[PDB]
Image (tube, rainbow over the protein chains, first blue to last red):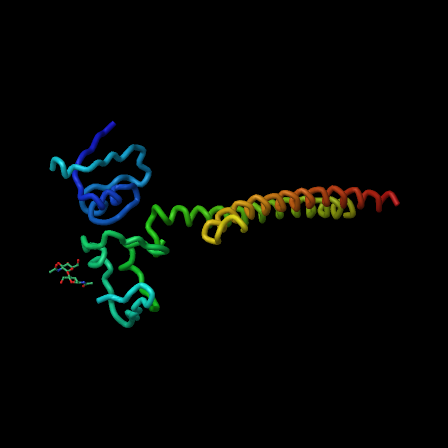
Length: 48
Length: 49
Length: 49
Length: 49
Ligand SMILES: *[C@@H]1O[C@H](CO)[C@@H](O[C@@H]2O[C@H](CO)[C@@H](O)[C@H](O)[C@H]2NC(C)=O)[C@H](O)[C@H]1NC(C)=O
């Protein structure tokens, strides 16, 4: 179980899903289109 | 100023080259949902209008 | 495959595959039924010979 | 078609069309196989006549 963690600006959380494309999915981190796994995201303005 | 939604402003972009990558790379576009075509390939197509 | 990217194209391709493969299964079934009819005619022709 | 509008109904219709069309292809295939059996019996009857 690889756990991969990073930060992204709120409305870009849509980009992460498998088969998406755009700034994160194109140039930073892409999920495989047959990904088995879970994407966990939560607000961090209280910290970051 | 844009149009109001009831009277949408329509412009024919035609007889011109269009790189859609420079659109899609704009961090402004919170929504860029496409149908029947995928953004990664738009530059491989040409369209009648 | 020019318009769409793989994750969407796979759904479109699967529908053409389904219909093209069902067209072929219909063809090969029909040719098997009709080949049995020709072999009946060939056995009859051999007997008449 | 009383419950749903077109964009949703078309998926529901496609499922019924698939299953109803496969029902007919099963019928017509089996009726062809069984028609060959009748034609064998008819040729035997003609020969016995
Ligand atoms: C609308 O105006 C903006 C600001 O003048 C243009 O912004 C450029 O957009 C491209 C594509 O994302 C970037 O590569 C440039 O770096 C941007 N320039 C600046 C100064 O921010 C934008 O090009 C214009 N819209 C269109 C469709 O051309």
